[PDB]
Length: 553
Length: 50
Ligand SMILES: [Mg+2]
Ligand SMILES: [Mg+2]
Image 1 (cartoon, each protein chain N blue to C red):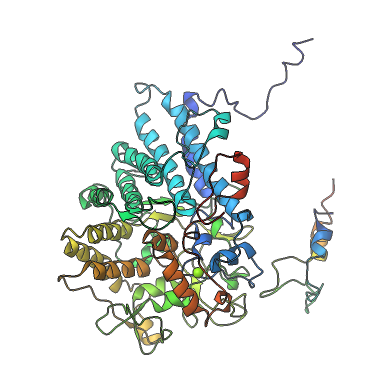
Image 2: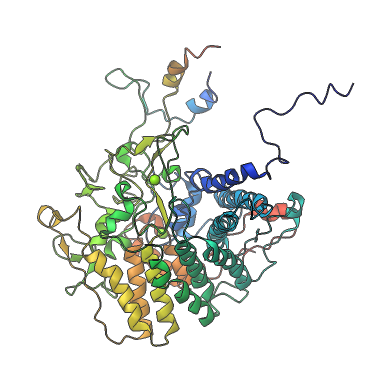
């Protein structure tokens, strides 16, 4: 009685022997984008903002140091365990992303280029997304497994190792995809969710920029700065490439953080959160659910630090205060200030995300922590409370896109790679730095009235096109990055690229403990803490194949 | 009964009242933990009848 057992079949399912079929191929593709909107978690967002509290830009926030324990252990660099659930969580989540790209890629390879001529352009998009995940993994773990053989069977996965490739051999495998996307992506994507050629180039460069700051040794310290790598960062940040895509700086800085201006000319590549779309409530950016301020009920995480608020101070010529900024807290009436601060930090006495009907104050309505963690509000991922684009799910979320590559990154990355090349091209990099600084100096749509209502003195000036030392131009480049990318969570990863991680974070730990007493027993450890531990669960399940990171055994 | 009601009744601080002072339903406020009145969750459940 054999016909009897073959009669019931699975219900509402494609079986993994029809998935490779051609009619599902674009289904695998769109599927591979979505997990960037759908596979993250309030405690593990793909902006990596949780793991940017380790830098000088922000605090954890919350009720207190007990609310989100494993994250206050990352902020102060004391108490991280190879077994903390959140480090394991992000390792598995990003590798889930790579599942959908490699499954898309598996089915794409068997397509006939004659029956399907978008074949290479989708392989390109799929390989571009694979490198997106790999890049973030490297930033977080350094010693990562390269999963880019999409024809691997599943049991072949138990033999993979994170030391198969050397650090510079790893970064080249990440580069190697971005490198492909550049060569096969079309120059304009009318569907803005897909990256254009310019995006892959931008991303190819960024990767070579991290690759150039060599860690060729057994430890995390720098072992050199490769010129052949930096010569690739300049190559793919060429404005000729960028212009082919229609990319550039926005008129006003705030345009990149407002729903009314999604996918403008600076959104080089972005994640397309959306509402009113058939999903249960989303596709919202749920991952930032903790960062919405107390005024909405919950939860007050991801607060800017004073060390960041003060870094927007400026002198009388409108330049930053490189040697004296953090001494005295920013006083609105006296000191000059970079406009970029009022699109980055929302401060007490000022309108919360430009809505004068909500003036931040210092009370139970704005600090869940009664001031333990301060009274500042990140603004680059929240929105106007009155926005039609803000729904309440588990936590509060918007459809405000997430920009992975802004174009100001294309320019400041280019400037850094010119300055460190010191082939006499430093004056072309100061011209880049000015483009970004001149823009911000004028970015006062929505805060123009702040001079007479709250007393704010705007003054930002570009640098005079003269001869500069390398070590000085690298200071001017770091500061432009500092103000331009506040709270956008590339911060800590910059300090680790520059090899300054230990010195800067420890200095910050000292300077700031008088202002946020959670930082009072903090201590970064050189050659240990520039990266996270390979998660214990993951080492332990590999049965010998995974090496841990330096300084964790 | 909804999943883990008892396990929710036991990690809700005794300061939070069952009723607010207008007679609606009590709940947390400010820094107090993100967790709802169990007695009110039992009310809002009371017609979910199979
Ligand atoms: Mg920090
Ligand atoms: Mg959107």
